[PDB]
Amino acid sequence: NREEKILNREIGFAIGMPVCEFDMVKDPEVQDFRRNILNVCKEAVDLRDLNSPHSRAMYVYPPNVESSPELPKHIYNKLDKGQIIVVIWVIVSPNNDKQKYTLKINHDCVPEQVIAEAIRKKTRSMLYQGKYILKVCGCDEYFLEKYPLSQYKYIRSCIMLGRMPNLMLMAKESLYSQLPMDCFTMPSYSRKSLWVINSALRIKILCATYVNVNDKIYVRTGIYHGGEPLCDNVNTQRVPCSNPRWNEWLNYDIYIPDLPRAARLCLSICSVKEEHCPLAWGNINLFDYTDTLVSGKMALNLWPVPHGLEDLLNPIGVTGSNPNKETPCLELEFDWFSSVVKFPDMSVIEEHANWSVSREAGFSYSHAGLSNRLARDNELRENDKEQLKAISTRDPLSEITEQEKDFLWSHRHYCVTIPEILPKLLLSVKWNSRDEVAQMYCLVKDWPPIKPEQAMELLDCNYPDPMVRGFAVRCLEKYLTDDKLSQYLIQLVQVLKYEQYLDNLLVRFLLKKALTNQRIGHFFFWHLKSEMHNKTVSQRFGLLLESYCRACGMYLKHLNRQVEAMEKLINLTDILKQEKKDETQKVQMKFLVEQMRRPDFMDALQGFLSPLNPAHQLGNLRLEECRIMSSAKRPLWLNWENPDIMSELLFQNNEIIFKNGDDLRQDMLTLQIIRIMENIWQNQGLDLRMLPYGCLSIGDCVGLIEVVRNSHTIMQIQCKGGLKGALQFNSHTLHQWLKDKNKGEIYDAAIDLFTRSCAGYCVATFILGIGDRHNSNIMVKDDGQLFHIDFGHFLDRVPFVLTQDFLIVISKGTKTREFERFQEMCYKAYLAIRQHANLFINLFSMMLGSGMPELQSFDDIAYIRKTLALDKTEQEALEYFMKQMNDA
Ligand SMILES: COc1cc(Nc2cncc(-c3ccc(C(N)=O)cc3)n2)cc(OC)c1OC
């Protein structure tokens, strides 16, 4: 149709590639995914239309709320007898005169209560009900739901910073008119044996093409469950890369029924010189998406070897044939049987598991042979029931011995009472045994649901099993809030890559949520779009962005404006850091102004939503304020007028830093972790103010960074311009600048705010291992709030040692009441993150599959164990932190 034609040009624009490339793809799974995922789209659209227009308004403008209405004592204590002074604005008559009405209301007041109060006071000045809604003055944020006013992030932030909440009273039909009508049109494209086999595992290696220049090459193979081998690495006989035709049948020490559903064939082509090196690699799922075992011949286009490849095989790598068909291919032949070998149904598995129970009690009572894995009845002592608890407490990176692993499996039936031990129990299973596995599948079909956070440990590279993964999705479906979903969106988008198939529960959960919450959808899109260049994931994400773009609605137009501006900034910075790179800053600027003033560049970058917070409108550009920065890689400091009619109550101007050349994934994770550390601290009752400024990677080493208003680097303060020098840098200079900025009842707050942000960042940088910190890495705001920029490296010793310049601001002139109070905060902060060690390990663990340099192995994540002192007791760790900290 005409509608469809127009749409695929639009989807194609936002996705980076045209829709018709997906049309021409002939792979059962791809066209099956393309079609099958449309019900999620329908489900999501129908949830939007289910309570039209309110539920549609909620989709586009979801309430931005904290996860709980409970205010920690220090947040509550800020309120005037548990009450908040709030200001309601009303735009009246033709001249759009802004009338304000200040109210003192309960912090837990519903928005509708607050509106009624504003109307009460509106009439009581001169001396309706559900016809109005509340909007945040200066940004596209609405308070459309019955949550208490304080539960909203804008209101809780206002309380904490001691800022006056300015809100605007808006007509419901004024917002409802601004809303478009959904039109999810269904696309054009939408219109045997089993476990019997008594054979061993054998696969033939025919030949390899596209291989040449420089001694002898062999094919190395392996059978894996995630990254754990289910047998021995079987290899082909060495051949020089002139005629690589082995045509030999490789035999493995696994029997066809003992193969788990998540079993993979991990192969590679290696070279020999005492010196072995991998050349090209490739992984295959031993079962397809319909659950059929691989039958016949196959041509696997292999992948280049990523630098720093520890082994000869890459089992953690992406499963499937490289899309670049002009790369080293490797033909294989697989054993044929009666017809088609499909994986047994859960019923067949249940009958075999109930047998692996009735005839296992017929193998312990009616066989003789011992296995320290046989579950014994009435032989579950309280002496070892506390031992299971002792194992369940341990961190995800804590090595579990063979003695402990055997003990756990034997007590599998008890472990249901302690559901948090599931990750330790699953790793205790012999996945190379169909008897143990069948018993486990059944325990998981009935396993009690665990917290979303614990269920995430099960969604990493260590747990490939579909039913283990399915349980984990069900836990996030039932217990994960939309707020916590926004927090872990980075790791959740990442774990998609580990999934064996295009169509899974994780993707359906994530897409549904993305298509039911435009805020979740926004970052979901950008997180996927930022990885389209990566040809390892480009397909999966390309299909996902298609299904998203079809059912996202009129927001696709808003995404296209963002994509167009982002490309013009890339193209501009491309020409600049190529044609004018070694030239002077005055020349680069001369060129920048000349180029930005072009008609096509002007309108692509004016009047669009900011990708950093889509609720922020970016109007006209303040070119007089747009400059190339003095900082490294030459970032582009951009300024935009805020077109909001009440911009003067939030920020008249919006400033974004456009970086082209540096990887921002590391800075993104650090700031996600910082934000999580801050929440842990705030809930726990410690007010360590952190500044997790917005950072978003938008492509291959391109990205955006939120400009922190009224802030300067440590160097900028220490100089006062350049009237001092690196030697002449007097230690008291920092405190003096702060003193001149804040005087009177203002000064005491400033020092407090400094010491607090100081204590938080000391603890944060130490745990995380954020090293190479200096005067151009640390920053301070006008109000004394400290923060850190450019997270160069992490995990690779005191990562941030206390400089005199800071301790002096902490007091005035090492042995002060302020330093004693300070030291305490750091000890208190350290102990709080230690109580959450299991979360941070998992969050980091889910990132190994992301192509990050300083997060490749479980040897990088182990650093968190050393800085948090997990092995030691809580009081023992304090002695460790005390020792590392007591060093000046
Ligand atoms: C770093 O130097 C400067 C910074 C800023 N301002 C701001 C405000 N909020 C944030 C940042 C920031 C954050 C992260 C990263 C990163 N990830 O690289 C880089 C910069 N920068 C202003 C400067 O001169 C006026 C300046 O040059 C001396």
Image (cartoon, rainbow, N blue to C red):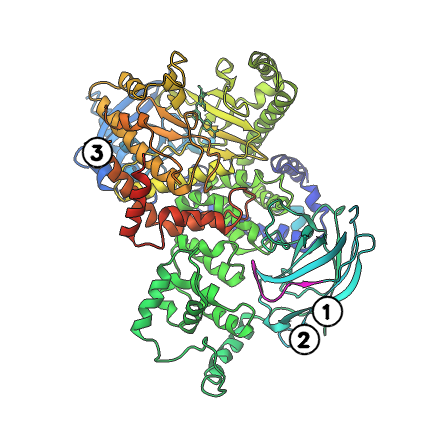
Asked if disc 1 and disc 3 are in contact, CB closer than 8 Å, the reply is no
805 or 281: which is nearer to us? 805
Amino acid at pointer 3: Lys
Amino acid at pointer 2: Ser
At a point 42% along the width and 77% down the height, the residue shown is 375
Query: Where is residue 195 drawn, in percent x and y?
Result: 62, 74
Query: Where is residue 405 drawn, in percent x and y?
Result: 44, 67
- Element type where label 2 sits in the image: loop
- Element type where label 1 sits in the image: loop
Image: magenta residue range: 227-235
In the image, is residue 323 above or below residue 98? below
Asked if disc 1 and disc 2 are in contact, CB closer than 8 Å, the reply is yes
Query: Where is residue 264 drawn, in percent x and y?
Result: 62, 61
> Residue pushed farthest left?
81
Instruction: Tell me if residue 558 is in the magenta stretch.
Output: no
At a point 67% along the width and 51% down the height, the residue shown is 277
Query: Where is residue 140 drawn, in percent x and y?
Result: 42, 30
Rendered image: mark on residue 199 = 2
Q: Which residue is mark 1?
A: 335
At a point 49% along the width and 13% down the height, the residue shown is 624
Q: Quadrant of the C terminus?
A: top left
Does the rendering let one see residue 147? Answer: no
Q: Point out the frontmost of discs 1 and 3.
A: 1
Amino acid at pointer 1: Asp
- Report how far apart the C-alphas of labels 1 and 2 lie in the structure: 10 Å
**For mark 3, does the 10 Å Cα neighbourhood hold few (<14), some (14 to 19), or many (20 or more) residues?**
some
Q: Which residue is mark 3?
A: 78
In the image, is residue 418 above or below residue 504? below
